[PDB]
Amino acid sequence: MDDEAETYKLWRIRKTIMQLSHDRGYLVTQDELDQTLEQFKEMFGDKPSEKRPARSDLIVLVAHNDDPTDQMFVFFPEEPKIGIKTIKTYCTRMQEENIHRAIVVVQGGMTPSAKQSLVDMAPKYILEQFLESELLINITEHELVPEHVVMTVEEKQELLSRYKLKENMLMRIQAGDPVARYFGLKRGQVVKIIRSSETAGRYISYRLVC
DNA sequence: AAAAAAAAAAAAAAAAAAAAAAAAAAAAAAAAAAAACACGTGCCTGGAGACTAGGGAGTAATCCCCTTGGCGGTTAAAACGC
Image (tube, chains in turn brown, green):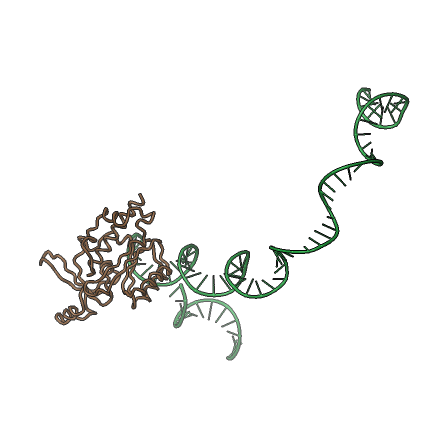
């Protein structure tokens, strides 16, 4: 009961993580997007109690299409509460492979001391965190969520020059939004929202991450 | 006829339900500093190996002294009763 449900939720979480990596412009193959539950059972195992697969066994490294040295790690700790010891273990793994992006998927909780740790290690390495309950549902696949596109700084400058817009008088989106966490949006970026309009067909808006 | 005390008129003064946001108290886990039986390490004094040689214990023979065994005579000690 626990093994089958754990394997099912691990496969669903891995599929959600792979779709998140595909949505962020990273080098993602089609078979990992279309990995079935039986494919996950054959590749990794079906009994998570006896380490088949282990929580550290499933570790995902993905690369970017344009810049191959820009890569992301995905970490699955087994413990419910995350201390600074395992964060420092991931960090000591993280400098020795010369990569600036990783996401740790917590299970139960992750301490405010480690919150402050992730705050003050931020402008060298990006170490995002995610809850296991939030990664059982793809956010962008919902019918209430329109299309979100991350936009570069040159197109942002073109948007500011075309409409005579300033950044403080733009439409805003909080940095703690689940959509912004899904795309990994930082403060100062502008996301483009394409939605269906019943009076014009489709509409495009621009939101500032704050 | 003038001075003092009590009575009364006139004038000033105090006296309804609901919801969001913030402050606060009890609690509670996470993380960073001083103790403490036994472990790490080096030294040495006592434990261990070998040879000699001797003196204290085992073995053989004897005996006689001490120990065991029986049989009988009152008889004081024991047993029974009130």
